[PDB]
Image: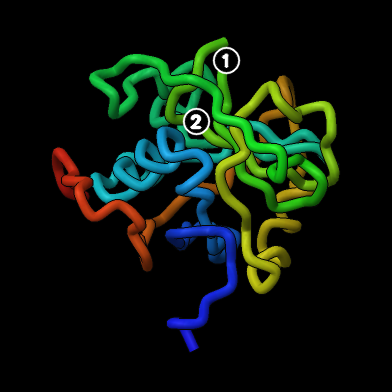
Amino acid sequence: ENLYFQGSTRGKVVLHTSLGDLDVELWARECPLACRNFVQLCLEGYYVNTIFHRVVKDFIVQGGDPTGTGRGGADTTFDGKPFDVETHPRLKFRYRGLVGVANLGTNGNQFFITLARADVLNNAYTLFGKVTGHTLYNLMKFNDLEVGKEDRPMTPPFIKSVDVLWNPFEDLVPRRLPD
């Protein structure tokens, strides 16, 4: 059982989307700044009702901007300052379902999830989580959306609620709680 957990990840969140749940396991040891910012926002209710404002087929889906415009998400947990990209030799964008920090140039609160292998994103973006094999079928529905101008889904899916099943940061205190 769990005492014998063999994964390299620490922490797990469930994004309950309008297209089904995505369970995100986190590389908290390797990417502590991206993971702390992401988990803390999830606890505070920042991502509730946020849409996925970009789908680029067989490439990425992007969300985590409360303005819904694609330009928001700069109000980070680190007193609103951007944070550094975090890389790791063993974390590469080799598969669908890999979760990265999006930057417009500097890291904020928006994230993206790969819909296919995407080597071009290596080293340039923090790869901080992974959608579990069991929930990839929901992720792949995003790949099937009708898209309009600027890669915007005609009907943007959205995050209904977020449950932090395993918070890997014993000292994180959310600044507020969900509305």
The picture places residue 171, in percent across and down from the top left corner, at 20, 48
Q: Tell me the element at label 2.
A: loop
**Furthest-bottom residue in view?**
1
Which residue in the protein does label 1 denote?
104
State the residue at coordinates (41%, 25%).
67
Seen from the viewer's position, the closer of residues 113 and 11 is: 11
Q: Is residue 62 visible?
A: no
Residue 66 place in picture, x, y as percent:
39, 31
Residue 166, percent from left and from top: 37, 65
Tell me which label, 2 or 1, sits earlier in the chain: 1
Type of amino acid under label 2? Gln
Pick the residue in front: 39 or 90.
Answer: 90
Q: Nearer the viewer, residue 99 or 68?
A: 99
Is 129 left, or right, of 159 in this rendering? Answer: right
Up/down of 15 relative to 147, above or below: below
Q: Residue at x 71, y 20 (%)?
A: 150
Tag 2–tag 1 contact (CB < 8 Å): yes
Q: Is residue 8 left or right of residue 10?
A: right
Read off the residue under disc 2.
110
Which image quadrant for residue 87?
Answer: top right
Question: Which image quadrant is residue 113 in?
Answer: top right
Seen at 39% across and 18% down, the residue is 74
Could you classify mark 2 by the number of other residues whose Cα lies within 10 Å: few (under 14), some (14-19), or many (20 or more)? Answer: many
